[PDB]
Length: 216
Length: 123
Ligand SMILES: *[C@@H]1O[C@H](CO[C@@H]2O[C@@H](C)[C@@H](O)[C@@H](O)[C@@H]2O)[C@@H](O[C@@H]2O[C@H](CO)[C@@H](O)[C@H](O)[C@H]2NC(C)=O)[C@H](O)[C@H]1NC(C)=O
Ligand SMILES: *[C@@H]1O[C@H](CO[C@@H]2O[C@@H](C)[C@@H](O)[C@@H](O)[C@@H]2O)[C@@H](O[C@@H]2O[C@H](CO)[C@@H](O)[C@H](O)[C@H]2NC(C)=O)[C@H](O)[C@H]1NC(C)=O
Image 1 (cartoon, helix red, strand yellow):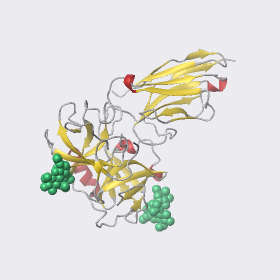
Image 2 (cartoon, protein in one colour):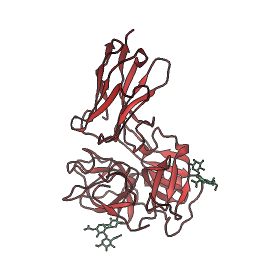
Image 3 (cartoon, protein in one colour):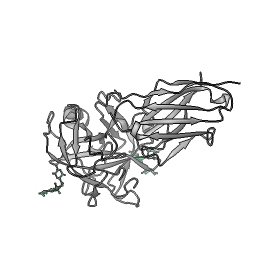
Image 4 (cartoon, protein in one colour):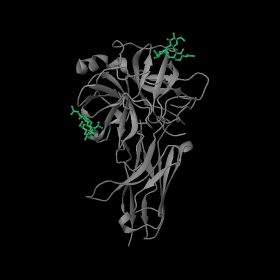
């Protein structure tokens, strides 16, 4: 997250860190005690058996007893097309069930087919690049929905008046709009915080019935 | 849409030099990692070299360190592979690669691959 701010500790208990060799590489969202959702490109050509799903984290540079670590049991995608950047969404089943508490909670999803209009105010977040290196503390950022320079197959956002936006390592992280998870960070154009192109998110509302068919 | 068109292959004499290029046609998606893999016939794909989106970090295979240099040009969304002191064991189809994941440059988890170009080092 470029030009964002440190989140309050455990403000977004549904926020997840996906790690490889102990290092954060993508975000995800807890959508049931035994399922997280992230971006399909986060597991494309990865050895899923080594992916550690970390729940209840805040500062990735500190030892945190609030954390709950799971492994990935199964992968569920729905027409992910890397060539055309479509349906960048994956549901990862966990090898167990999370203990729901103050620091680990399930996210709420929108109704199937709910489209957001221009100007809707959202909150983006993640442990990706700051512009400075990877963030230690979870970062959040106020963003606004735009339908220009964006496809019907994405939810796009922009920061009005400043050089800020999502960056590398924020992929898979949620976009929260009116309390619901409406986006999964997918890609940026013209580099991070360009002020030319909006950041692109997988449109979660287009997949709700399918997510629900899996997580029940 | 997302494409990797390479150029700069061909023949060279042992000890020679060659420069390869790879463009990501259009400002369609900013890819964190860009690099080069290579494959000799009937052998496995080999990471050769890689680079950050910023250019602050690079990595190479130990068999090409000091001889090969990888550079990037975000303005022309290109990557280049300067190959010097070429050995016949460097003969392979060189593939330009790209990927969005924030992972080590040497991690063989690249999603985007070019068609490859033939580099043939003589003897
Ligand atoms: C569910 O998985 C966790 C995590 O397993 C680790 O991460 C995987 C990606 C893989 O690398 C595994 O080999 C790792 O073990 C399990 O957590 C482990 O549990 C044992 C016993 O408690 C402990 O010795 C390990 O250190 C734990 N690892 C971590 C990082 O917490 C957990 O046991 C699994 N649960 C079920 C239901 O099988
Ligand atoms: C910057 O964003 C925060 C948070 O945005 C809200 O909460 C997200 C989780 C998501 O639901 C977004 O779509 C929301 O817009 C704003 O904080 C809210 O502000 C209002 C009024 O100021 C307040 O009543 C709410 O309780 C706040 N919500 C939370 C969870 O903090 C903040 O105001 C935004 N700032 C600007 C200048 O836009």
